[PDB]
Image (cartoon, rainbow over all chains, first blue to last red; front, side):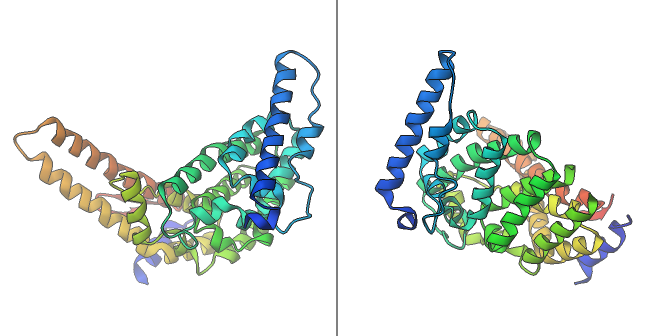
Amino acid sequence: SSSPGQLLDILNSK
Amino acid sequence: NLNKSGGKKFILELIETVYEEILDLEANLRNGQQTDSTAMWEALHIDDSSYDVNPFISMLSFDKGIKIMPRIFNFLDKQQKLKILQKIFNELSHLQIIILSSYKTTPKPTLTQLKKVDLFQMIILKIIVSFLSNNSNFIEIMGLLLQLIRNNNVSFLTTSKIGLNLITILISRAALIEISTWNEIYDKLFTSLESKIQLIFPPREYNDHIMRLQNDKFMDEAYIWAFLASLAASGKLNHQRIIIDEVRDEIFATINEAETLQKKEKELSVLPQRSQELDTELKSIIYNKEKLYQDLNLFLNVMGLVYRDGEISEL
């Protein structure tokens, strides 16, 4: 269920 | 092409026949008499696969064909209505309205062409929405999604406003309705879109052309973010990761547009003298700024994210 954690990082990372 | 269905004179003749049959059904019903929709159904040529492009699909290239569609639906049963939807989704790439609303096939649509697109959107999509909301089960919705994915280049359909909105309706309805078949069908749809998700946003030269013709100060892209919100909502974390990655530059471009509007609002609101025209200007800026915030947050909130005070953070 914890989608915001990783998703916020992928939006910046690449 | 119109010739791939029998020619212009043949299709225009079919439309006239359809109108005659509807007028007869409407007159009988109005006079409180018995109605038989067999002649009208037969005049539609849905089960006719005699041509490269079905005659019903070509009838939808004309405003007259489009405008009679809600009236046609008043005299049909569930399976007849489902056969129409099945035909539309089966030959969606051959639908002239898709070719006209695609920035790829029609990069410079005329005002007359844009009016046809808005008409098809207002009439045809309202019919599809009502029918699926009331007269459709899991198997039937899944059936329509498979018809779309198997008979069309799905990426091409997403370059069209009509195509994109039709897919959003199917996804949104499927999401309301076990988990298993839908997860499999969503993944088949996701496969046809993967590495091409950015193509749903039309080029700037296309937006400019539309904005100039319609006297729009900003391009309405709410339907794009609504599609992305429905695609994200029915996807697992791995689908969401791909979506965010593919539209990252579009997320940042929208934020820049909203921040430019916020700056304009600040610069104009500080002015001492404010005429009725400046008040109209400010109201227009605030409206368009809030619109961009709301459209982006429709997509972001679905993934537990939010755009607030110039930054994207966890909700």
